[PDB]
Image (cartoon, rainbow, N blue to C red; front, side):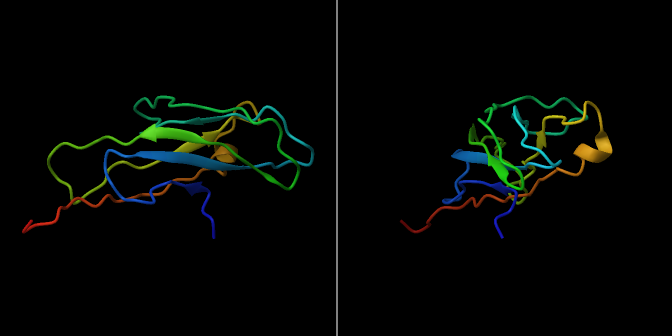
Length: 122
């Protein structure tokens, strides 16, 4: 039912640009403003990196925000194709200075597999 994360992986093909979008839910009880998004591929424990961001004009109460970001898929190694290893993670700006347990509530991520094959014969 429209997952928090939707990729433009309409045509499964490694080395294709995919649209990474994260649905941000406006909580609290008042109209929120200045709610940017920072996406980074990998784990925060090692050392993630920012790919891009987009500040929204404004998000209404009881509503949700929708950002648009593009990223180039690339992680091939000419070996072990029977496994992705390219997960996706996204985090929303801290609406409460510092709070892991809280932020850890608005966390979303899904695994995706890429098809690798070619037509034989001719």
